[PDB]
Image (cartoon, rainbow, N blue to C red; front, side, top):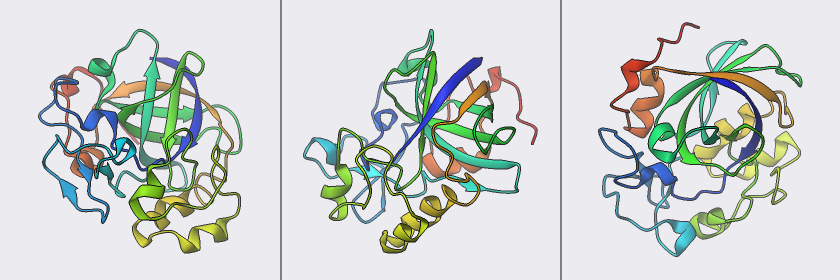
Amino acid sequence: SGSGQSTRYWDCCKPSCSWSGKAPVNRPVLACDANNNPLSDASVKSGCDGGSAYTCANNSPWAVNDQLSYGFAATKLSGGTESSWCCACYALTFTSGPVAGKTLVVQSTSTGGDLGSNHFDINMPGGGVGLFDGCKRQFGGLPGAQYGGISSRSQCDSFPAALKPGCQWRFDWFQNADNPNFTFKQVQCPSELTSRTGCKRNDDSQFPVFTP
């Protein structure tokens, strides 16, 4: 459905698609308590608003081969609304930086800030908390700059264990790419992603199957 710019983030906040009535889905994205246990109760208040609900650690990216990874993102799309992108999946093909040519299929779990025509803020632990430091409340905070997060792969060594794979993915398969550009198209969600969030759009079948 177009081209866009990526950034990186992990702020630990309850994802905005974890709330009820936001999109036509079977159920909202599962958030987690501070100890990474899934919350079936979608009314729990976000740890970024004085509450106790956080992003589940399984909202992390991973590689299945040197060409293809799966992950999650906050999206802000031209012509769209939360009701059209929450729990939708998109295949991104990177067009710049060291990852140019690689493919990342993400599910949207949240609404991102406006940046360019179709911003994808890609989840990766240690990518930066930005404006809301929920990770401070969840477990005392993550190292790293407010925007961009950590700068060395060793800094992943002190993360909560469940956050270390996604932290290291950023330096391994993602090659520490700094805000690469991409083209993207909406696709049916691989079960790899909807099994983690539990959230599947009623219109999922309206879009093409992803072929690796």
